[PDB]
Amino acid sequence: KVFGRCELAAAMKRHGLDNYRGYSLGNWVCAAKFESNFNTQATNRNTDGSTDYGILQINSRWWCNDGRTPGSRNLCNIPCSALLSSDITASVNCAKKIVSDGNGMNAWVAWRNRCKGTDVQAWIRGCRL
Ligand SMILES: [Cl-]
Ligand SMILES: [Cl-]
Ligand SMILES: [Cl-]
Ligand code: NA
């Protein structure tokens, strides 16, 4: 599923991400935009052999099991493939654990390089929610 901008904001809000750990909704929508272009099916291989999965490109190195990332952890206790559903629940629940872990949303490279310090409220402008 490829979410619309306001559609995803609403879905994320419903799942409790608005101001989660102090991060406004615009931050999460921005991160999703640049991580996956709002596409729940997005997968991307990393150089170390891990893979990033789904709307928020969650990494098999730490957070999910794909059975092909030697030495990795599965800290969200989920198969990585469950992070590719049209329903974002699994991705959101795992994201809440990631953002609570120490360095906040800096864990998302695209957020740090493209969203952090920007006018993130623009991502939810005109959205019902
Ligand atoms: Cl679609
Ligand atoms: Cl915002
Ligand atoms: Cl959803
Ligand atoms: Na593995």
Image (spheres, grey):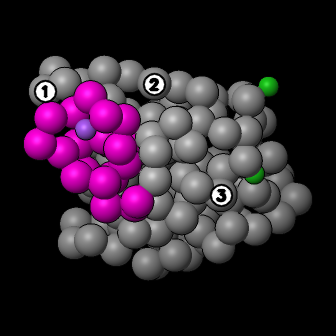
Dominant SS type (magenta): loop
Q: Secondary structure at mark 3?
A: helix
Residue 78 image point, x, y percent: 46, 53
In the picture of the structure, the residue carrying the numbered disc 1 is 48
Q: Indicate the secondary structure of the residue bearing disc 1.
A: loop
In the drawing, what numbered circle is on residue 89?
Answer: 3
Q: Which residues are magenta?
A: 57-77
Q: Nearer the viewer, residue 84 or 26?
A: 84
Using the rendered image of the protein, determine whether residue 32 is visible from the camera's viewpoint.
no
- Residue 114 in the image: x percent, y percent? 37, 39
Residue 28 % position (x, y): 53, 55
**Residue drawn at x 75%, y 68% as measured from the top left:** 14
* Residue 93 image-quadrant placement: bottom right
Location of the N terminus by quadrant is top right
Where is mark 2, residue-wise?
43
State the residue at coordinates (37%, 48%): 64
Q: Earlier in the sequence, mark 3 or mark 2?
A: 2
Disc nearer the start of the sequence (3/1): 1
Alpha-carbon distance for marks 3 and 1? 27 Å
At 83% from the left edge and 64% from the top edge, which residue is drawn? 129
